[PDB]
Amino acid sequence: TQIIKIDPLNPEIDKIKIAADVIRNGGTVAFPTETVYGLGANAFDGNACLKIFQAKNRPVDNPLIVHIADFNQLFEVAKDIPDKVLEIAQIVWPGPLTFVLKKTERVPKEVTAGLDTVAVRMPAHPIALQLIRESGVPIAAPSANLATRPSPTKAEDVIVDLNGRVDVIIDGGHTFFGVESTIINVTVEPPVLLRPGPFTIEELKKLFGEIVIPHYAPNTRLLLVENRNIFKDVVSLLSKKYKVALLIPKELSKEFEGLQQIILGSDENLYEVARNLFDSFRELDKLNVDLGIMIGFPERGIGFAIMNRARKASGFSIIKAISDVYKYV
Ligand SMILES: Nc1ncnc2c1ncn2[C@@H]1O[C@H](COP(=O)(O)OP(=O)(O)NP(=O)(O)O)[C@@H](O)[C@H]1O
Ligand SMILES: C[C@@H](O)[C@H](N)C(=O)O
């Protein structure tokens, strides 16, 4: 694997070209975006895309998001797009919002998992956009991690997971949001939120008033305490019988000195928490503890995506009442 360091905000186009040549040659390139790093291949090349599944050891029926750098490309991969969706795509892209649309015959089965639809987004990251532009083709690209590990948000995460398994890894620093793009299905009416992300429910509702609102997790047991009023008592109860690691905001650090802590960021900035979430899950597994205990966060804005990933990462081991401790431990 060639690891190429490229400045994320002013990328050296010559370095981008090295990676684009690999994409055009049917190879795989891991690269940063504003959400998480993605592992990409030419979206029109089914055989190249199968290499993404092989590298991640991913079940072949879990479809891939296609990344485009301009609107001409949107029409190469999707069709029968509603006028309103097109107008909105033009104001939200490049950005962390993925649309599920009807696919064209140029999108291979390897990308869509046989579905009649294709998920597409335009990444708000200079390296991703330039990689796509120089490759001259849309790039299919799920998160760049091994199958059960948390989505990567920094180059080192990708290296640890995929070094030796992919052709190129672009080391472009830490990703901006740290959580995967919001996914909305607009082939159905009203549209449906398939995955919360950096593009908020609050904003989607202003654009799609009718929208309907319905594992990458650590291996160490992880409990999520959604009720902040019982957090201290839950920690006291559990730390008596277990070696614990607390995933918490810096504002609660002093309250728990003596116990292993994984600081997520500040309560006053949920984007900080979102940015450090997946790497905090990785840290949990590096530590040698019996269980991680994460505190809940507000669901305003990106808080909703934070909680969605946390619930899943905890295998839905949620503590809302102190007596719930009986259920999951
Ligand atoms: N045509 C589709 N219809 C419905 N959902 C789709 C479709 N295409 C892609 N998706 C979804 O997109 C998800 C993949 O997101 P993507 O970020 O490309 O890869 P990932 O690594 O699976 N994401 P994540 O699990 O958070 O790392 C799939 O697991 C589906 O949830
Ligand atoms: C790689 C990154 O773009 C991922 N596919 C997402 O949609 O967040």
Image (tube, rainbow, N blue to C red):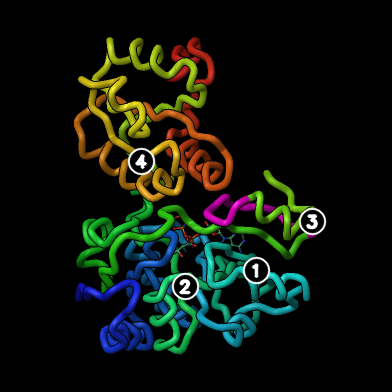
Could you tell me how far apart the alpha carbons at marks 4 and 3 are, in whole angstroms? 36 Å
Give amino acid for label 4. Gly
At horizontal 73% and vertical 65% (from top left) the residue drawn is 187
Give amino acid for label 2. Ala
Could you tell me how far apart the alpha carbons at marks 4 and 1 are, in whole angstroms? 38 Å
148 displayed left or right of 169:
right
- Numbered tag placed on residue 265 in the rendering: 4
From the Cβ of disc 2, is ligand 1 less than 8 Å away?
yes
The x and y percentages for residue 218 are: 34, 39
Could you tell me how far apart the alpha carbons at marks 4 and 2 are, in whole angstroms? 32 Å
The first of marks 3 and 2 along the sequence is 2
Q: Which residues are magenta?
A: 189-200
The x and y percentages for residue 306 are: 48, 43
Q: Which residue is mark 2?
A: 140
At horizontal 35% and vertical 26% (from top left) the residue drawn is 252
The first of marks 4 and 1 along the sequence is 1
The first of marks 4 and 2 along the sequence is 2
In the structure shown, which secondary structural element does the residue marked by tag 1 occupy? Answer: strand
Could you tell me how far apart the alpha carbons at marks 3 and 2 are, in whole angstroms? 27 Å
Q: Which residue is mark 1?
A: 117
**In the rendered image of this protein, does residue 172 appear above or below residue 189?**
below
